[PDB]
Length: 351
Ligand SMILES: CC(C)c1nnc2ccc(-c3ocnc3-c3ccc(F)cc3)cn12
Image (cartoon, rainbow, N blue to C red):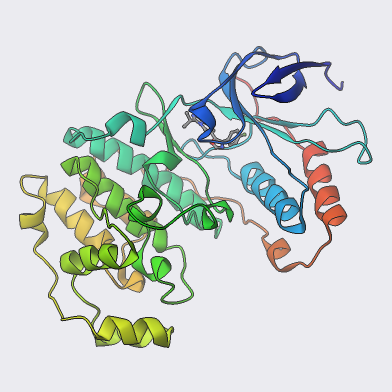
């Protein structure tokens, strides 16, 4: 019942994978990590196979490995990247070193489809509907994406969409400095560490994506953190007395107060000629105070999506046990937990 594995070198690594996966070919030019498109002969799908780099290099990497595998195993929703397969060539814990993860190969990201382009109003509707449908599922598991942006949205030829890279630490270290897209979708409370934030950060990111799909333009392309914040307050107004109380960082509060106050702008004059229902939705997403943003479950019931909305086809998730997050473990302990999670994996049904 353990498959037969075969070896090859791909992008200077030895990849050892079950024979069911044929014709492995690097994709994304390193942008997604060590990932190969392959043909899965068992399901007949084109799949993306990721070989984790340095999975057990430090306590921090070990845990990051475990976390990503936990997150992927839990997700079973059409608009969320999940696991078709997870394997290692190792036959015991003692020889366990590498982890390979397998999911559907969508083929492109939103970003590398829609660069510089206003999309038709039904393409916007359909794409945002799907982001919000996947997001309602993710949030119902108490998972926060934290890094939603076009590059993290994997889209296929039929404009079907799956959300990538949710709930990871990873986005931390790579650069958020200067004129960089890694920062343009971030909610201001997380960009400037205003407070203990939560899942509402992601609705901000949805707003920013939706605007950009409408206009063809990045909504807040700041040259840095401070220039971006000025872009943001110009549109959505400076914080009022109520939000200021909630900015638990005295440092941030004190800098915000130094800015000339500005009223919210009129979204109908900003998004000239766009569906009024779209405007109204963006107004509900791009609210400076996170507590007041629309939720994904609520946005799905908004009239903009009336063509796609179906409350019996917008599932929620099983509860996700993230107690491990507060556990203080050694490398070998995270590695063994990870091993158990590999070994116990159950394939989805092939129809
Ligand atoms: C072209 C590109 C955007 C793309 N298309 N489909 C996909 C699918 C996945 C990934 C991916 O990006 C970063 N990590 C992964 C990943 C995650 C889990 C897994 F099992 C295998 C790979 C990229 N994809």
